[PDB]
Image (spheres, coloured by chain):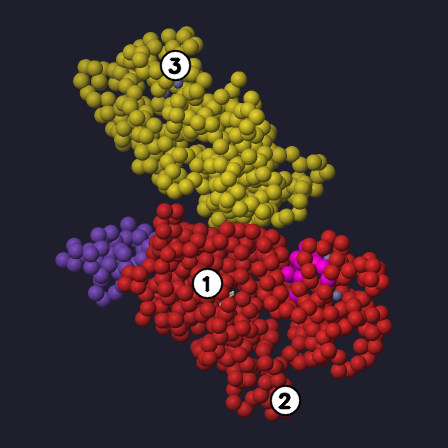
Chain colours: A red, B purple, C yellow
Amino acid sequence: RTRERLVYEVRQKCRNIEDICISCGSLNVTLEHPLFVGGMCQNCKNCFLECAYQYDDDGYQSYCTICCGGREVLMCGNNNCCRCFCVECVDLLVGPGAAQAAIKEDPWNCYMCGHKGTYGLLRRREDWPSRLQMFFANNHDQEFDPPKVYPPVPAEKRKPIRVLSLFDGIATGLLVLKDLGIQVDRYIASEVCEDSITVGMVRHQGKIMYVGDVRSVTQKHIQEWGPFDLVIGGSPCNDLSIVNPARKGLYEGTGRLFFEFYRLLHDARPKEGDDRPFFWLFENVVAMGVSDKRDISRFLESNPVMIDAKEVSAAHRARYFWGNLPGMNRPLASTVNDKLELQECLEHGRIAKFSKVRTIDQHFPVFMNEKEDILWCTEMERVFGFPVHYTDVSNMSRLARQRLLGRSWSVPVIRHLFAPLKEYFACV
Amino acid sequence: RTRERLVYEVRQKCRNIEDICISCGSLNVTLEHPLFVGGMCQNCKN
Amino acid sequence: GRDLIAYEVKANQRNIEDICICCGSLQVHTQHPLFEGGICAPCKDKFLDALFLYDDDGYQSYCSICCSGETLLICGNPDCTRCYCFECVDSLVGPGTSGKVHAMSNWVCYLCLPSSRSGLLQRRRKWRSQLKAFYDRESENPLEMFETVPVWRRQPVRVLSLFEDIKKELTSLGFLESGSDPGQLKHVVDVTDTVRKDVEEWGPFDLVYGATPPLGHTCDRPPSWYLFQFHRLLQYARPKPGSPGPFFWMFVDNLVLNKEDLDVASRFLEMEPVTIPDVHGGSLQNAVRVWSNIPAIRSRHWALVSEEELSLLAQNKQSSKLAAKWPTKLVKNCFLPLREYFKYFST
Ligand SMILES: Nc1ncnc2c1ncn2[C@@H]1O[C@H](CSCC[C@H](N)C(=O)O)[C@@H](O)[C@H]1O
Ligand SMILES: [Zn+2]
Ligand SMILES: [Zn+2]
Ligand SMILES: [Zn+2]
Ligand SMILES: [Zn+2]
Ligand SMILES: [Zn+2]
Ligand SMILES: [Zn+2]
Ligand SMILES: [Zn+2]
């Protein structure tokens, strides 16, 4: 309401729209809104960090794009666009009579997809993908020192890498290390779900020395399993995301398991004065809490890097990566082997309407034989850059196997991250 | 007895089975046991 | 036979190391750490039990040679907690010495001053180290154990105390200064923004302390969050590797995190909780769960207090209308062994 009074005052040319927070009408303007014209307070920044990449079961956004809240949202009819604009923001930025008349417009495009681009009170700021990329470098609220850069070991002195992988899953980390041609001395992997154990056992030919639960692992185990050169892991994002209908908590269950990664990182870290190269990668999902993100950054003593897989693969897989791997910041390059269109990842005889996929109306992405159908499991493997037929090991159901594929890291993203480790360890 | 305590410590994943002599439990592991997994001390070799 | 040794050594010209000075046994498991002589196996066990046991007022609980609390002689050095017994002083130092010592009332003990002529009892050199080595080789499952500091080598103790100020407690334990404006303790309420650089800027620390709040919630942040923040800032306040100086840490719980979060905490602090109750009339008034490395923290444990009774206590104390008080007196005596490591003074 105060929002609406302030925008009323702005249309009289008495107040600048850039001097007011367009999300909630706050006067405490610190930032500028990245997509559209207006200011941006810090509470709306925290709400924007939490809510922007949240999507309903629909596939469209959980909340409004402008204020990350709202009451009733207006979903976009344009293809592959999932944005929603609540009625209260369109009462301001387009007018109090144009929302009602725009609902009646049956082919309705949203204002990020509006072919014209310019409107009266609302105009779209031009370099908005650049500002969306800069907005996560704008997260300097958590200020830290940069990760310590170790000088490279000569090529004749290099040795096979040793990896402690927590929350292994289907052994994406070891696979990506074998794709890069790095010699792996040993790969210790703690994991609980039998199916993922079985996927890793078969696809990596008994090389992985498997363990039990992460919680059972003691520092004595860490010491006695040799010095580790690379510790990798990712917290469960089944409960942490808004996509699961059963959100009883937020950091019950998953939160604990993050601290298990934290502890075994301090157990596997070499002492001060031991200047041997040691590296670590944590992974989490972007649709997370702010104070959650703060606590993670503070425990791991680092600024997260957001990496979206759209730059290299055929999915929208935006994930945080904490770590000290060299060149974690540097921009993503997609090789010619990587498929940037969904249609290339399809089987023959199938034609996709989408160019990128959202796997958790249009819930089933494929029009084959004038019929709506789910991606096949081997295609979901192709979307994330896995080798073909990667998960067809054991007699498991399709729902379980899709669920086994959907938790996994995106393979070309993890190749992009792990690639400068070749400079430090031996090759095949 | 001691070697049974040793194997108990191995099944907890605190010790490798290849670092212990599976015949008599000796810590003086020079050889590996030829047929099965584990070390092999020289007295057990004789 | 405690009395027989005076014949055995003098007339039979026999080494003190071949007999047990603590009781008069002739079969010795090893040698006595503090003084010249052997020691037999039950006395060895008795000694290791009693080792760092003190009394509530401040002084050592048992007799420093033989661990007899039945009779006690208080030493007259303000920087010495060593208390003895009569049977030893007359048995080991000659027939009429304990009564003379008792009549002196300004008597420094053997470890204080050796200048006084001694009949049979000889003080081992370096004995602090010998004590440490004895505990190492002779304790079953030995623990994090630091050599005791000579009294002139005792510096003031540097305390970090998270979520609870312990200035009042340790000042009343004479460990902290009442006359200083530069505080020798750094209390922090909110640690949320704290970085490793910040804990390092605040100086090195000797003791780290952190505790969950009582039942009246100052804030709604869950009790696991305090534990994890403690673990982090604890890993920050650790001394740089290669440090011989004694570093300690003590986490305290006022029954406020459940069994699941308790299991998580037991894992992350790498030992099982020590429950230390307040029992009045036989009745469980209060209790507190601890984790620390402080000597003889684990022999204060009470295995009589069951988990169901602690759940009943938590239920009864949550449903009362009284404001929550910090249970000072339960963890107060759990800092007494640091007397033997750090500089005391009390006016
Ligand atoms: N306590 C625990 N210990 C080990 N793995 C666990 C676990 N709890 C859950 N997990 C598993 O850890 C995974 C969480 S995320 C897995 C992603 C992984 N990088 C991959 O590419 O497969 C799930 O497979 C989940 O079943
Ligand atoms: Zn705002
Ligand atoms: Zn809105
Ligand atoms: Zn649109
Ligand atoms: Zn043998
Ligand atoms: Zn004895
Ligand atoms: Zn005595
Ligand atoms: Zn004395």
Q: Residue at x 53, y 61 (%)?
A: A305
Q: Position of residue B45 (x, y in %)?
A: 16, 59
Disc 2 versus disc 3: nearer the observer: 2
Q: Position of residue A171 (x, y in %)?
A: 44, 69
Disc on res. A327 = 1
Rendered view: C274 above or below A167: above
Number of other residues with Cα within 10 Å of mark 1, as a class: few under 14, some 14 to 19, many 20 or more = few
Rendered view: A285 above or below C111: below
Q: Amino acid at mark 3?
A: Val
Q: Mark 3 — residue?
A: C108
Q: C338 or C307, which is in the foreground?
A: C338
- Horizontally, residue C32 falls left or right of residue A107, namely left
Instruction: Kindly tell me whether mark 3's CB lies below 8 Å from ligand 8.
Output: yes
Badge 1 element = loop
Q: Mark 2 — residue?
A: A371
Q: Position of residue A408 (x, y in %)?
A: 51, 70
